[PDB]
Image (cartoon, rainbow, N blue to C red; front, side, top):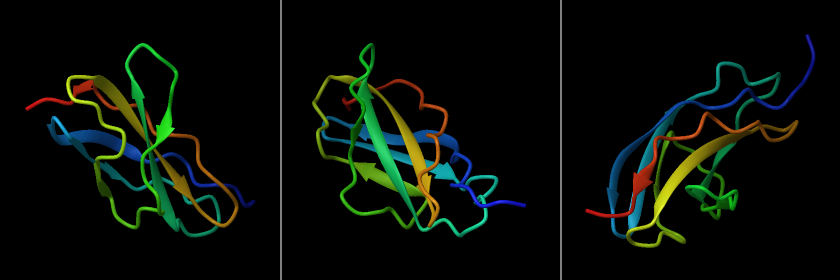
Amino acid sequence: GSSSPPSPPLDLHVTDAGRKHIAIAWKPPEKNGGSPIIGYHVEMCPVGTEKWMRVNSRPIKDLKFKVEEGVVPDKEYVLRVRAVNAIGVSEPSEISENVVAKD
Protein backbone atom coordinates (compact mmCIF):
# COMPACT_ATOMS: atom_id res chain seq x y z
CA GLY A 1 0.00 0.00 0.00
CA SER A 2 3.15 2.14 -0.36
CA SER A 3 6.33 2.24 -2.51
CA SER A 4 9.64 0.93 -1.15
CA PRO A 5 12.86 -0.69 -2.40
CA PRO A 6 12.55 -4.47 -2.77
CA SER A 7 12.91 -6.84 0.14
CA PRO A 8 16.27 -8.66 0.11
CA PRO A 9 17.23 -11.44 -2.30
CA LEU A 10 16.77 -14.92 -0.86
CA ASP A 11 18.61 -18.22 -0.64
CA LEU A 12 22.07 -16.97 -1.58
CA HIS A 13 24.52 -19.81 -2.03
CA VAL A 14 27.90 -20.56 -3.57
CA THR A 15 27.72 -22.84 -6.59
CA ASP A 16 31.40 -23.08 -7.46
CA ALA A 17 34.74 -21.56 -6.52
CA GLY A 18 38.32 -21.45 -7.74
CA ARG A 19 41.54 -19.58 -7.17
CA LYS A 20 40.12 -16.81 -9.36
CA HIS A 21 36.33 -16.92 -9.17
CA ILE A 22 33.41 -17.45 -6.83
CA ALA A 23 30.12 -18.38 -8.50
CA ILE A 24 26.90 -17.66 -6.66
CA ALA A 25 23.16 -17.91 -7.15
CA TRP A 26 20.10 -16.60 -5.36
CA LYS A 27 16.33 -16.30 -5.54
CA PRO A 28 14.22 -13.20 -6.14
CA PRO A 29 13.04 -11.04 -3.27
CA GLU A 30 9.75 -12.00 -1.73
CA LYS A 31 8.45 -8.46 -2.46
CA ASN A 32 9.47 -5.83 -4.99
CA GLY A 33 8.13 -3.05 -2.76
CA GLY A 34 5.85 -1.54 -5.43
CA SER A 35 8.05 -1.23 -8.55
CA PRO A 36 9.78 -4.00 -10.53
CA ILE A 37 13.24 -5.26 -9.65
CA ILE A 38 15.57 -3.96 -12.34
CA GLY A 39 18.90 -5.39 -11.21
CA TYR A 40 21.04 -7.03 -8.58
CA HIS A 41 24.38 -6.07 -7.05
CA VAL A 42 26.91 -8.40 -5.45
CA GLU A 43 29.24 -7.48 -2.59
CA MET A 44 32.19 -9.47 -1.25
CA CYS A 45 33.95 -9.19 2.15
CA PRO A 46 37.03 -11.04 3.47
CA VAL A 47 35.93 -12.90 6.55
CA GLY A 48 36.59 -11.16 9.84
CA THR A 49 36.57 -7.67 8.27
CA GLU A 50 33.80 -5.22 7.34
CA LYS A 51 35.40 -4.31 3.99
CA TRP A 52 32.40 -4.98 1.76
CA MET A 53 33.16 -4.22 -1.87
CA ARG A 54 30.83 -4.21 -4.89
CA VAL A 55 32.12 -6.76 -7.42
CA ASN A 56 29.78 -6.13 -10.38
CA SER A 57 30.14 -3.19 -12.77
CA ARG A 58 26.66 -3.24 -14.28
CA PRO A 59 23.37 -4.30 -12.70
CA ILE A 60 22.99 -8.08 -12.82
CA LYS A 61 19.85 -9.07 -14.77
CA ASP A 62 20.05 -12.73 -13.74
CA LEU A 63 19.87 -14.81 -10.56
CA LYS A 64 23.50 -15.92 -10.67
CA PHE A 65 26.89 -14.25 -11.01
CA LYS A 66 30.51 -15.31 -11.45
CA VAL A 67 32.54 -13.09 -9.11
CA GLU A 68 36.02 -12.41 -10.44
CA GLU A 69 36.93 -8.79 -9.68
CA GLY A 70 39.08 -8.55 -6.60
CA VAL A 71 39.16 -12.27 -5.81
CA VAL A 72 42.46 -13.12 -4.10
CA PRO A 73 43.55 -16.78 -4.16
CA ASP A 74 43.44 -18.52 -0.79
CA LYS A 75 41.51 -15.65 0.80
CA GLU A 76 38.25 -16.49 2.55
CA TYR A 77 35.11 -14.49 1.84
CA VAL A 78 31.42 -14.05 2.45
CA LEU A 79 29.10 -12.53 -0.12
CA ARG A 80 25.75 -10.79 -0.13
CA VAL A 81 23.34 -9.58 -2.82
CA ARG A 82 21.13 -6.48 -3.09
CA ALA A 83 18.08 -5.89 -5.29
CA VAL A 84 17.26 -2.56 -6.95
CA ASN A 85 14.07 -0.99 -8.22
CA ALA A 86 13.02 2.57 -9.15
CA ILE A 87 12.54 3.47 -5.48
CA GLY A 88 16.00 2.40 -4.30
CA VAL A 89 18.29 -0.37 -3.12
CA SER A 90 17.26 -3.28 -0.91
CA GLU A 91 18.96 -4.30 2.27
CA PRO A 92 21.35 -7.13 1.43
CA SER A 93 20.50 -10.79 1.46
CA GLU A 94 21.58 -12.99 4.33
CA ILE A 95 25.31 -13.47 3.79
CA SER A 96 26.67 -16.56 2.08
CA GLU A 97 28.48 -19.45 3.63
CA ASN A 98 32.20 -18.79 4.02
CA VAL A 99 34.09 -19.59 0.79
CA VAL A 100 37.84 -19.87 0.16
CA ALA A 101 39.11 -18.88 -3.29
CA LYS A 102 40.82 -22.21 -3.95
CA ASP A 103 40.26 -25.28 -6.06
